[PDB]
């Protein structure tokens, strides 16, 4: 069936150029138009522009004209979106979606899965992992909390498991925050029986693939 | 461009409830209103296309109405998978323009947070920085006020918060607040307090520690 497949996540510096892509499968490429949508972090959707590969005609939203170029390659059924000079404010998720022409009544019925673009002055950096140790100040009833602070890494993402995936109940891994450095930072916490605490070993397994940083941090009481 | 005004931005409802969301356009767009659902981390999904046409495979609990400038989407008998963000889209004229979205949240009973405070670790202190963390665990509704006090001085602009998505099992939220100071500043003060205000608490809850102890 119809699939639109986008290229992988991108991390860039301001001023750098970038071309991302969307390849169509399962239908005739020249029978439709391909449109590009921006979704800035935590925001809604914006239509950037579109191309008819059949007619080699592009249309742009006035707010994006001169900032980006949309193009297509009929031979590989691929559409492209490109910037010649990225800005930090271009940080967003980018989606391609299928549509029709003047007179068509169905818009964006199939979408790519979409492509994250991060633009920052920051450079790749692995996190430091610090314990958030259980004590009395973190023992509600017969419930204790503990965690790991995964501090000062770039870019996203990091993954965290507990006890190599054996501990899943009561785990909360928070969305990362972007610090004024920034460097991202997140915490992962788990609530456990206070009678734990004690006799059960708690280890957070942290993986930051961009810097190839992998850390197993034992978290002990007091 | 045609401006699209979607309301409400946020709506709580119970599983099984019926809700109606509206979109108003600044120009007459005839029947060219389209509705999308988007879950976190996913592409939007087309539900209904121009002329109130439900897309193949979309449940009939989704219906829409409207012509000209005023439009609605009704979801009947809300299922757990329905609690996502909805966007309207006008496809009358270029540029295509979308409403700002409606996030639907699962309504449940009030639950007060359990609150925990974590002093900075000795390992972190060795590197010249101190992060103090306050955790509010498993609470509802999402609205919560967290105030940091260092020797009774209210900290402002000094902290960052992060909130989880609504839990798929109990429909609660959790929140962390991190207060960041220099090692130097951390060591010149004694009492570190996180004060939490929430509708599930009859009065604010304070968690604190004295540095050293
Ligand atoms: C060959 C050039 C292709 C260029 C790139 C494609 C861009 C698509 C442009 C169409 C955008 C205007 C939106 C109008 C859509 C109408 O077809 C429907 N609302 C039906 O018209 P109604 O029944 O409401 O009058
Ligand atoms: Ca129409
Ligand atoms: Ca129209
Ligand atoms: Mg209601
Ligand atoms: Mg009703
Ligand atoms: Mg449920
Ligand atoms: Mg201070």
Image: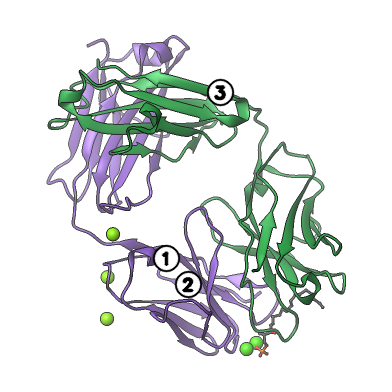
Residue A183, position as x, y percentages in the image? 55, 30
Are circles 2 and 1 on residues that touch, CB within 8 Å?
yes
Q: How is the image coloured?
A: by chain
Q: Which mark is residue B6?
A: 2
Counting from the top left corner in percent of width and height, residue B133 is at 34, 28
User: Which of the chains bears the disc numbered 1?
Assistant: B
State the image quarter where residue A125 is shown: top right
Q: Secondary structure at mark 3?
A: strand
Residues at discs 2 and 3 in contact (Cβ within 8 Å): no
Q: Give the label on residue A213, or none.
A: 3
Q: What's the CA distance linking mark 2 and mark 1?
A: 7 Å
Q: Are marks 2 and 3 on the same chain?
A: no
Q: Colour of chain A?
A: green
Letter of the purple chain: B
Quadrant showing the C terminus of chain A: top left
For the N terminus of chain A, which image quadrant? bottom right
Residue at left 62%, top 64%?
Answer: A111
Rate crowding at label 2 as few (under 14), some (14 to 19) or many (20 or more) other CA atoms within 10 Å: many
Q: Which SS class for mark 2?
A: strand
Residue topped by disc 1: B9
Against B62, is B41 above or below?
Answer: above
Q: Is residue A159 above or below residue A203?
A: below
Residue B106 in the image: x percent, y percent? 30, 61
Q: Kindly identify which numbered label has been placed on residue B57.
A: none
Task: Judge: label 1 CB < 8 Å from ligand 4.
Answer: no
Q: Nearer the viewer, residue A189 or A3?
A: A3
Query: Real-space Cα distance between discs 1 and 3?
Result: 40 Å
Q: Nearer the viewer, mark 1 or mark 3?
A: 3
Left or right: where does residue A203 sit relative to residue B41? left
> Mark 3 belongs to which subunit?
A
* Position of residue A195 in the picture relative to residue A132 (left or right): left
The answer to which of B80 and A93 lies nearer the viewer is: B80
């Amino acid at each position: 069936e119809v699939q639109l497949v986008q290229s992988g996540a991108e991390v860039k510096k301001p001023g750098e150029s970038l071309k991302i892509s969307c390849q169509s499968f399962g239908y005739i490429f020249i029978d439709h138009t391909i449109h590009w949508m921006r979704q800035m972090p935590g925001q809604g959707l914006e239509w950037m522009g579109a191309i008819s590969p059949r007619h080699d005609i592009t249309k742009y939203n006035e707010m994006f004209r001169g900032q980006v170029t949309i193009s297509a390659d009929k031979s590989s059924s691929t559409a492209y979106l490109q910037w010649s000079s990225l800005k930090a404010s271009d940080t967003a998720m980018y989606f391609c979606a299928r549509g029709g022409f003047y007179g068509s009544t169905i818009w964006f019925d199939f979408w790519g899965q979409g492509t994250m673009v991060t633009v920052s002055s920051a450079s790749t950096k692995g996190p430091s992992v610090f314990p958030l140790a259980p004590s009395s100040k973190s023992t509600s009833g017969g419930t204790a909390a503990l965690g790991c602070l995964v501090k000062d890494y770039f870019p996203e993402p990091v993954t965290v498991s507990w006890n190599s995936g054996a501990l899943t109940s009561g785990v909360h891994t928070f969305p990362a925050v972007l610090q004024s450095s920034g460097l991202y930072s997140l915490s992962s916490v788990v609530t456990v029986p206070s009678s734990s605490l004690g006799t059960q070993t708690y280890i957070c397994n942290v993986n930051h693939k961009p810097s190839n940083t992998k850390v197993d941090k034992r978290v002990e009481p007091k | 461009e045609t401006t699209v005004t979607q309301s409400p931005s946020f709506l709580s409802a119970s599983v099984g409830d019926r809700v109606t969301i509206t979109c108003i356009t600044t120009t007459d767009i005839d029947d060219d209103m389209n509705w999308f659902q988007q879950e976190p981390g996913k592409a939007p999904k087309l539900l209904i296309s121009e002329g109130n046409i439900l897309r193949p495979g979309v449940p009939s609990r989704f219906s829409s109405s409207g012509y000209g400038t005023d439009f609605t989407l009704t979801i009947s008998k809300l299922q757990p998978e329905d609690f996502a963000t909805y966007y309207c889209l006008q496809s009358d004229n270029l540029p295509f323009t979308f409403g700002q979205g409606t996030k639907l949240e699962i309504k449940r009973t009030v639950a007060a947070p359990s609150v925990f405070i974590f002093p900075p670790s000795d390992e972190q202190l060795k590197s010249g920085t101190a992060s103090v963390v306050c955790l509010l665990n498993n609470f509802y509704p999402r609205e919560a006020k967290v105030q940091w006090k260092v020797d009774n001085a209210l900290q402002s602009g000094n902290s960052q918060e992060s909130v989880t998505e609504q839990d798929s099992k109990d429909s609660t939220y959790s929140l962390s607040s991190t207060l960041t100071l220099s090692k130097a500043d951390y060591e010149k003060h004694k009492v570190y307090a996180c004060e939490v205000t929430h509708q599930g608490l009859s009065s604010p809850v304070t968690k604190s520690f004295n540095r050293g102890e």
